[PDB]
């Protein structure tokens, strides 16, 4: 509904429509893949 | 006919007779460096991948 | 002489010098923005002078893109080393090289003069009509600057393409990076000129393209048909630099040279056909949206191959060599930072995610991480690598671990919170905002003042 | 992919039992900012700079051949800082092949 | 395992300790590190080990700190960042006692798993 | 000539006049002023003040200062 | 402790590495060739056996 202080709200917050829920879950679905892509690559940044 | 170049007329960079007798040794070191390089490539590729 | 010089290496120095000068104006504008956004209220801009903020954000974007980073990464480092990398005496077109830098300076003077003399209003750096065509004369002046800049960019692109005819050695990856950017410019600029002329026609010639029965969405197609190729015209030279630095400093031959080259070619072709991911919220047809979303995600493949080829360059390097040199640190930092920017780009590429994140500060943080952090650091790293060849001194940068650490920490303090407020949500191109978004905006503002202070320590 | 030069076992056989790998230092030396003398004028400071080029340095091996300062790219081959005119004599990229012609030899 | 199974023409050190040596070092001073593991003044060359006598390919390893402080030094004599320590002493120990290595790795992973899961959950 | 071998020989040989550096920094300083001076001028033109007082466009407590 | 040493000695024996199947075309070292290099060579990372 309205922004609240010091909230991460990663991927969205307070959906009030089925489409709004879809948007939040699409981001949540891809987020672990993004973490994998980052962690897997960064771990090899070294001599 | 083409112009001819004679290598026997080229002045050479200065090298002492002591240095000239070590040519085989330096070549020997170079081969061992290439052998160690090639083997290490396989070793490192396996470790890091 | 100074202005008459045709030496390609001197002109390269001029490009870097001018980028830093114009860059001072760019950074100042950025400080104004962040100061204003420190809390809710008016801080340094009156509510009756809100048009100035709109002009500040517009000029910030335009100057940093076309007058700072592009002249620095495509004009500065390229004009200095490309003829050397090509084992050629000098650049193919000497007189054209001279006029290009003069043109850039003259267009800069026009822009800043328009700040002083014209009424200050803004329409974004994307100059969307009808807003751009109902404005005052400052918009006309900005259009003249862009067109003039376009002339310099195209002639410089012609100059680099001619190296293929004279190159006496091997086309290294960096040379390939510049050539492809030149191709991207030759194909994208003529379209930009056309749409800019149409903006002028509506502003100055009573044309009616951007009034009812004329589609305003037309502008966005032609603009972004140049817009996105521009973001790769700005990043590809940076990639070329990163390749040289990693290979040289680690004493390791580039791995997958041909894949690096073919990755750059691929990014260009794909980057020329994905522009409408900037137009997701206009209301395009379902199949168009799916095409553009699909092709946009494909760009990650070639971009990913380059990243992993860079990583193996740093892996396995000798431990005895000192790794604290600023150039090496910046090159490594680029990989770490670019992945963040690219991944967030893939997130916004999904159109349904984009509906929530369009015109929000998440987009800001995305392109800042790539440009304000990645591109800047790449240009710094490239100049630092060539410090001996260029010969500049009177700075403490070459070995300064404090500068690198402070820059990395504080730059992330500015833009990481901008990802958070993107789901809060705080729109872009605004100055006032709700009181519940102050915390994150305040943190980013503290980051901006700190970064500026660190820029003074180099001297 | 490149994996070094190929070695035949015959080439790894020493001519003496005491042969080991030559321990020659390939660190060129200790350096810093080039330090110009106050007395030197512009011309003589140019000579000083030209005599401090690392890319003109080398390491001499036990047989008298020298391994030069080498780089992957020709950017490191010009004088530092770069002079106005660098590659007056075209740099030569040497390619190798197995082709030969009789005129080059004599019996 | 480069010296053990791959290459037989590099000198092979003896492990003095499977733990780093902690020493205080001063900037502007040069230190010499034992690369054979037989010196009695570890981690430094004592003048009587292989390194000091230049025997069997062993030579002292020159090292110099940038700043004063306490630095960890390699006891296993095989760390990649030798003379400094980077964890290779533990790695080389696992090669020599693979059963012990598993115990420590399981314990470390167990703690890491619990903490990260407890905080995120 | 030896003096002409290096581009910008005086600067590279560390003999250049410092005024050249001062002009470069001054030019950058002037460029920066193009963002601040019009801000002050525009604020005064539309308000009568060169710079606002934080939150002076909102309702303030009686003791606010 | 007896079982501890037993399993420790059982694991150790099984893990002792066998010579690598080189995936590269290198020569055979001449017979009777000892240590030729020195410890000042660039360090080669110590890698665990598979
Ligand atoms: C009734 C009327 C009827 C009709 C009449 C119609 C008439 C029609 C006429 C048509 C023609 C008119 C035009 C004629 C042009 C003639 C050109 C020519 O042939 O000149 C030969 C002539 C050769 O001179 P010379 O007689 O041999 O001797 C020259 C001297 O010895 C000096 O020797 P030098 O050349 O070696 O020295 C030059 C140099 C010497 O160097 C220095 O001064 C010190 C070193 C540099 C310091 C650091 C500067 C900052 C870094 C810049 C980096 C990029 C540089 C790029 C290259 C330079 C580009 C200018 O310094 C400069 O002069 C300029 C330096 C750069 C200034 C700009 C830097 C950025 C500042 C940004 C500030 C704001 C933010 O050229 C020149 O030397 C001067 C050319 C001047 C052109 C000026 C054009 C300026 C345009 C500005 C914008 C205009 C719009 C807005 C203006 C608003 C004003 C309020
Ligand atoms: C038993 C211990 C482990 C317990 C846990 C195990 C869990 C299961 C793992 C799988 C099985 C493991 C089995 C290992 C057995 C040993 C095998 C072996 O060969 O042993 C010898 C071998 C080493 O032997 P050696 O090579 O002979 O020499 C000994 C040396 O010690 C040489 O050692 P080294 O070089 O291998 O040292 C390891 C070092 C090697 O790697 C490095 O040092 C690389 C560090 C590069 C850092 C670059 C700067 C990054 C700064 C980014 C800041 C971004 C700010 C802005 C973000 C904006 C976002 C919007 O690893 C790290 O430092 C960890 C880096 C991990 C990735 C870092 C990035 C995390 C990102 C998290 C998500 C972020 C999301 C938001 C961002 C955007 C997402 C799209 O040991 C290992 O392989 C040890 C690996 C240890 C891994 C520990 C990972 C801990 C950190 C986790 C992530 C952080 C968050 C945690 C909560
Ligand atoms: C992003 C920032 C941070 C970056 C950090 C990272 C940096 C990493 C490293 C980057 C390195 C890049 C590569 C560097 C290569 C350098 C090569 C080089 O040195 O070339 C030699 C080149 C020239 O040396 P040279 O060969 O001996 O040249 C001899 C001359 O050609 C001949 O000598 P001359 O004496 O005969 O010269 C002629 C001279 C003759 O000069 C004089 O006679 C001067 C007399 C004194 C005047 C002083 C100024 C007075 C101002 C008064 C203002 C009054 C305001 C009143 C207000 C009242 C209000 C109520 O000048 C002129 O006649 C023309 C001057 C034109 C240019 C200056 C323009 C100033 C601004 C004008 C604005 C106008 C706005 C108008 C608006 C109108 C609107 C209607 O060097 C320079 O030009 C200086 C470069 C210095 C910096 C080099 C880089 C160092 C490393 C970076 C440091 C950080 C910089 C940060 C940016 C600046 C921040 C502010
Ligand atoms: C219950 C316990 C069971 C224990 C079974 C142990 C089996 C074992 O280790 O066999 C090794 C054993 C060798 O024994 P050894 O006596 O030490 O002989 C070694 C010789 O020197 C020479 O041996 P060789 O010449 O026959 O070659 C063997 C060597 C040849 O090695 C190579 O050529 C390298 C192999 C690794 C390459 C990996 C490349 C990855 C590239 C990634 C690229 C993309 C990155 C970016 C991705 C971005 C995505 C967004 O193999 C390895 O090094 C294998 C390393 C292990 C590979 C594991 C791959 C899957 C991951 C498994 C993780 C651990 C899971 C534990 C689960 C526990 C239960 C929860 O092999 C054999 O007996 C036949 C082979
Ligand atoms: C140089 C600058 C630059 C670069 C490189 C990019 C790169 C990318 N950008 Fe761009 N972008 C901008 C600058 C840039 N962008 C700017 C300035 C804007 C805003 C303009 C405005 O609106 O005014 C913008 C806007 C923008 C939007 C608009 C969002 C909105 O308007 O709401 C989108 C969405 O499609 C997008 C997507 C992408 C993608 C998908 C990439 C890809 O190139 C990213 C590719 C990289 C990776 C993917 C990471 C590396 C690869 C791997 C680690 C391999 C593994 C990863 C996967 C398999 C996914 N960008
Ligand atoms: C590459 C271009 C570039 C660069 C460097 C930056 C740098 C910065 N930008 Fe950026 N910014 C844009 C391009 C850029 N920006 C664009 C295109 C927009 C959108 C415009 C629009 O909305 O219309 C934008 C918008 C934008 C906004 C949004 C205002 C709004 O529309 O509401 C904000 C503030 O939040 C901001 C802040 C900053 C800050 C704090 C920095 C930096 O100050 C962070 C700190 C980093 C430094 C101070 C180093 C920079 C140094 C150089 C650039 C010189 C390099 C020269 C050499 C190495 C020779 N930027
Ligand atoms: C680089 C050179 C090649 C570029 C080719 C780009 C073609 C991309 C195809 C995109 C696509 O499907 O086009 C749809 C899209 C419009 O979609 P909607 O507005 O939703 O309208 C559809 C029905 N009303 O088409 C366009 O905008 C095409 C624009 C013309 C591109 C012309 C390029 C010319 C290059 C020379
Ligand atoms: C105080 C703000 C920062 C001032 C500053 O650093 O200015 C530096 C800059 C360059 O000076 P040096 O680096 O010492 O160059 C001369 C040769 N070594 O100084 C000036 O330009 C002096 C005038 C500054 C006016 C600012 C308004
Ligand atoms: O723009 O990506
Ligand atoms: Cu785009
Ligand atoms: K505000
Ligand atoms: Zn010893
Ligand atoms: Zn150790």
Image (cartoon, coloured by chain):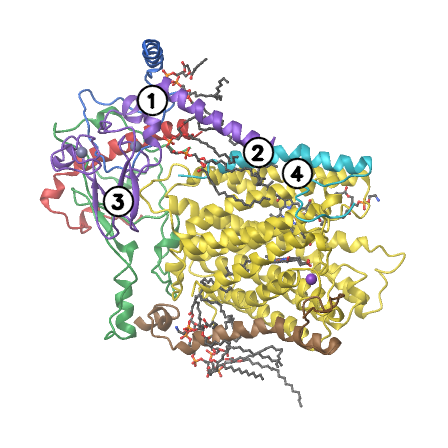
Chain colours: A cyan, B red, C yellow, D green, E purple, F brown, G blue
Residues at marks 3 and 2 touching, judged by CB atoms closer than 8 Å: no
Distance between the alpha carbons at the discs numbered 1 and 2: 34 Å
Task: Kindly identify which residue carries mark 4.
Answer: C297
Secondary structure of the residue carrying numbered label 4: helix
Q: Residue C282, how many percent across, how many down?
A: 80, 48
What residue does disc 2 label? Answer: E119
Label 3 belongs to which residue? E24
Nearer to us in this view, A22 or C84 = A22
Precedes in sequence: disc 1 or disc 3? 3
Residue E15, by quadrant, is top left
Q: How far apart in space, not on screen, are marks 3 and 4 (Cα)? A: 53 Å
Q: Which residue is mark 1?
A: E95
- Residue lying at 36% horizontally and 13% vertically, measured from the top left: G11
Specify the quarter for ligand 1: bottom right
Residue C87 visible? The answer is no
The chain under label 4 reads C
Q: Are marks 2 and 4 on the same chain?
A: no
Specify few, some or many for label 3: CA neighbours under 10 Å numbering under 14, 14-19, or 20 or more.
few
Marks 4 and 1 sit apart, C-alpha to C-alpha, by: 44 Å
């Amino acid at each position: 509904d309205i922004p609240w202080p010091a909230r991460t709200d990663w991927g969205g917050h307070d959906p009030a429509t089925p489409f709004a829920e879809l948007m939040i879950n699409t981001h949540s679905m891809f987020w672990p893949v993004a973490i994998f892509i980052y962690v897997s690559a960064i771990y090899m940044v070294k001599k | 006919k083409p112009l001819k170049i004679y290598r026997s007329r080229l002045p050479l960079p200065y090298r002492t007779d002591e240095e000239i007798s070590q040519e085989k040794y330096v070549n020997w070191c170079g081969r061992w460096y290439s052998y160690r390089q090639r083997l290490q490539g396989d070793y490192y590729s396996r470790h890091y991948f | 002489f100074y202005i008459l010089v045709n030496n390609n290496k001197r002109i390269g120095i001029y490009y870097i010098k001018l980028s830093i000068i114009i860059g001072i104006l760019g950074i100042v504008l950025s400080y104004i923005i962040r100061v204003e956004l420190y809390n809710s209220g008016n801080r340094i801009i009156k509510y009756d002078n809100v048009n100035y903020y709109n002009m500040v954000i517009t000029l910030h974007g335009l100057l940093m893109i076309f007058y700072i980073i592009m002249p620095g990464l495509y004009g500065g480092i390229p004009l200095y080393i490309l003829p050397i990398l090509s084992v050629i005496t000098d650049i193919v077109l000497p007189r054209i090289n001279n006029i290009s830098i003069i043109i850039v300076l003259i267009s800069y003077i026009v822009v800043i003069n328009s700040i002083v003399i014209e009424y200050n209003i803004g329409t974004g750096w994307t100059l969307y009509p009808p807003l751009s065509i109902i404005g005052t004369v400052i918009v006309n002046m900005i259009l003249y600057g862009l067109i003039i800049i376009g002339i310099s960019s195209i002639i410089s692109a012609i100059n680099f393409m001619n190296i293929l005819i004279v190159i006496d050695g091997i086309i290294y990856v960096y040379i390939w990076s510049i050539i492809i950017t030149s191709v991207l410019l030759i194909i994208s600029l003529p379209i930009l000129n056309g749409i800019l002329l149409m903006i002028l026609s509506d502003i100055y010639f009573n044309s009616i393209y951007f009034i009812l029965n004329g589609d305003v969405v037309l502008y966005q197609h032609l603009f972004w048909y140049f817009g996105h190729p521009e973001v790769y015209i700005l990043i590809l030279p940076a990639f070329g630099i990163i390749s040289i630095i990693l290979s040289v400093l680690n004493n390791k031959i580039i791995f997958g040279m041909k894949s690096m080259i073919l990755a750059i070619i691929m990014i260009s072709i794909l980057g020329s056909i994905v522009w409408a991911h900037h137009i997701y919220t206009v209301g395009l047809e379902l199949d168009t949206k799916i095409y553009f979303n699909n092709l946009t995600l494909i760009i990650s493949i070639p971009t990913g191959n380059k990243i992993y080829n860079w990583i193996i360059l740093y892996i396995g390097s000798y431990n005895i060599l000192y790794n604290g040199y600023q150039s090496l640190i910046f090159s490594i930092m680029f990989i770490i930072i670019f992945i963040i920017g690219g991944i967030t780009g893939i997130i916004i590429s999904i159109d349904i995610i984009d509906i929530g994140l369009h015109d929000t500060y998440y987009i800001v943080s995305h392109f800042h991480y790539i440009l304000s952090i990645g591109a800047v650091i790449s240009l710094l790293a490239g100049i630092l690598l060539l410090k001996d060849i260029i010969g500049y001194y009177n700075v403490i940068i070459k070995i300064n671990k404090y500068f690198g650490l402070l820059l990395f920490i504080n730059i992330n303090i500015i833009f990481t919170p901008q990802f958070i407020i993107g789901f809060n949500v705080m729109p872009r191109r605004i100055l006032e905002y709700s009181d519940n978004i102050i915390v994150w905006n305040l943190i980013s503002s503290i980051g901006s003042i700190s970064t500026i202070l660190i820029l003074l320590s180099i001297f | 992919i490149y994996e070094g030069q190929t070695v035949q076992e015959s080439e790894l056989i020493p001519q003496e039992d005491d042969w080991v790998i030559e321990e020659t230092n390939f660190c060129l030396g200790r350096n810093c900012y080039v330090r110009f003398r106050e007395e030197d004028d512009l011309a003589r400071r140019a000579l000083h700079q030209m005599d401090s080029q690392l890319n003109k340095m080398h390491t001499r091996l036990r047989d008298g051949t020298v391994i030069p300062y080498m780089s992957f790219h020709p950017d490191e081959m010009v004088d530092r800082p770069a002079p106005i005119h660098t590659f007056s004599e075209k740099p030569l990229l040497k390619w190798t092949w197995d082709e030969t012609y009789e005129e080059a030899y004599d019996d | 395992t480069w010296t053990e199974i791959w290459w037989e023409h590099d000198p092979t050190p003896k492990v003095a300790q499977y733990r780093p040596y902690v020493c205080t070092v001063e900037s502007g001073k040069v230190y010499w590190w034992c690369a054979c593991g037989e010196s009695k003044t570890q981690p430094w060359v004592d003048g009587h080990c292989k390194c000091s006598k230049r025997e069997g390919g062993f030579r002292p390893r020159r090292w110099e700190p940038e700043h004063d402080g306490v630095r960890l030094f390699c006891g296993c004599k095989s760390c990649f960042s030798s003379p400094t320590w980077n964890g290779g002493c533990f790695t080389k120990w696992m090669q020599s006692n693979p059963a012990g290595g598993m115990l420590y790795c399981f314990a470390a992973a167990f703690g890491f798993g619990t903490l990260t899961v407890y905080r995120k959950f | 000539n030896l003096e002409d071998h290096f581009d910008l020989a005086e600067y590279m040989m560390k003999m250049h006049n410092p005024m050249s550096e001062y002009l470069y920094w001054i030019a950058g300083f002037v460029s920066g002023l193009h963002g601040i001076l019009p801000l002050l001028h525009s604020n005064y033109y539309f308000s009568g003040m060169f710079l606002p007082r934080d939150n002076d466009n909102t309702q303030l407590c009686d003791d606010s200062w | 402790a007896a079982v501890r040493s037993q399993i420790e000695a059982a694991v150790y024996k099984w893990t002792r590495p066998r010579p690598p199947r080189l995936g590269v075309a290198v020569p055979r070292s001449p017979p009777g060739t000892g240590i030729l290099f020195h410890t000042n060579m660039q360090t080669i990372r110590y890698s665990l056996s598979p």
